[PDB]
Amino acid sequence: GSLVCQIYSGLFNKQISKNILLVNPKTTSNNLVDYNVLLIQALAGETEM
Amino acid sequence: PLTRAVLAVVRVRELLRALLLLPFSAVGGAVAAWQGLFNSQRYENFLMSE
Amino acid sequence: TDIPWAEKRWTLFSTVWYLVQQLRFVGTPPALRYVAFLGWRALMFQVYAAHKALVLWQCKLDAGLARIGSGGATATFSKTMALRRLHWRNSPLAEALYALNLYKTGRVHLLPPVAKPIPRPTFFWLF
Amino acid sequence: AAVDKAKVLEDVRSIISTQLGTELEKVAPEAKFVDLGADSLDTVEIMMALEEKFEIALEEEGAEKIATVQDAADMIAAQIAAKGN
Image (cartoon, rainbow over all chains, first blue to last red; front, side, top):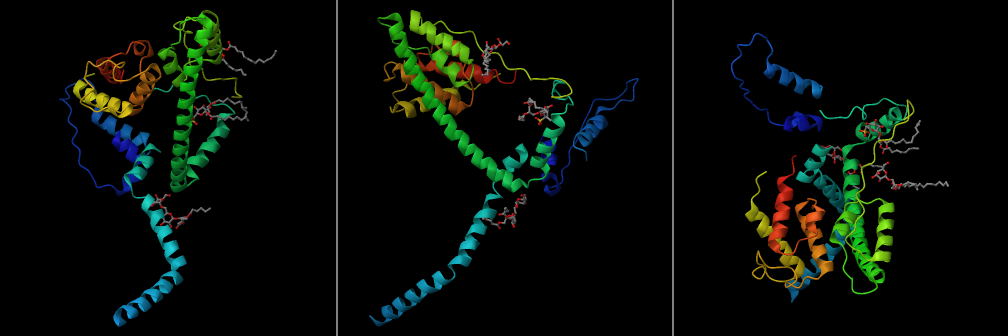
């Protein structure tokens, strides 16, 4: 939520760059769905970056 | 008595010198007020709500 | 994520409200918007103070009316009705019927049910 | 869902003292309102000051039966607790 409200208010281009670590328990599913990549692409598409 | 007379003269001429530049310093103070509104945390809260 | 599909109807009224809103959001600089925001806040504080004064006045008035109603002792009012008046939870008809009930039978604790929220009006492709 | 009832109580008592004009030692958690000098038209203004300070809305049916400071505190805490849902 903080990332979204920052990107929409235009204040993102002047913040200090961040590092964030996303962990998700092991992937041994029959599927190749990965919710890290999906969540970050949803963040980048909701804000149109 | 004499040195405070010279000080009184410099004080009167300081009155004049302060008043002759009063429009310039007036616009300067207005600009200072203007650009002071736009670096608070209040303006940041407004930007995030918008 | 929770938008009711009625706030996403494309109608002829909304494609003009789009222009009003796009002016306010993209065609006006944020600094003037900020100044207007401050002014509107101050105005709303004054208006709220006025409304609170009026609500207390209404409480005395109806506490006085219940006296005529009962003819005798009753002088209290209802705090429930005061709080409901402050949060805009009464329709005007409910206020009138409460006033009448007070004037005729005292009975300060009999309250109209409550107002329900107004649904969004829709016509057709029009609005 | 979990409210620090202690903080709510201190703030209630401070608001009550500032509204009535009596000092904070006299406001006890079991003190009724009638003896602190409160008369109907002011057991309401106290409710409005409370809501205005805490930024919440009071449940009216229970708000009809507020007569001691502890009931005020418990009403406010049950309101703050039920905020998300």
